[PDB]
Image (cartoon, rainbow, N blue to C red; front, side):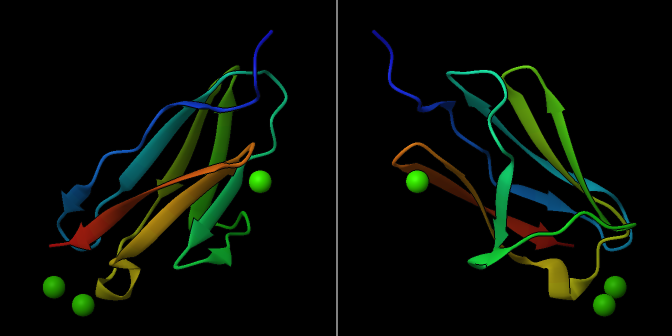
Amino acid sequence: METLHITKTMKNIEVPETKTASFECEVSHFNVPSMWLKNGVEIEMSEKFKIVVQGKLHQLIIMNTSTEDSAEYTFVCGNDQVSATLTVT
Ligand SMILES: [Ca+2]
Ligand SMILES: [Ca+2]
Ligand SMILES: [Ca+2]
């Protein structure tokens, strides 16, 4: 029928320091866990990183960006994973 897979990939993004950035990923199925990675390290929800789901849409909101947040961000689902880069300023 249908594999559990990523249906729409993420986009590279640049924002000025201290502003908010985001990444979005769309997947095939509902109730998928939001497996977000920063340089391969699992991201935990905090005051800074917001992990948001709307049905098949998954979004990482990165608030109060600093230079250090310039990284590769990854979404994992099925046997897929997609990545994009954040450049801060
Ligand atoms: Ca600066
Ligand atoms: Ca800085
Ligand atoms: Ca997997």
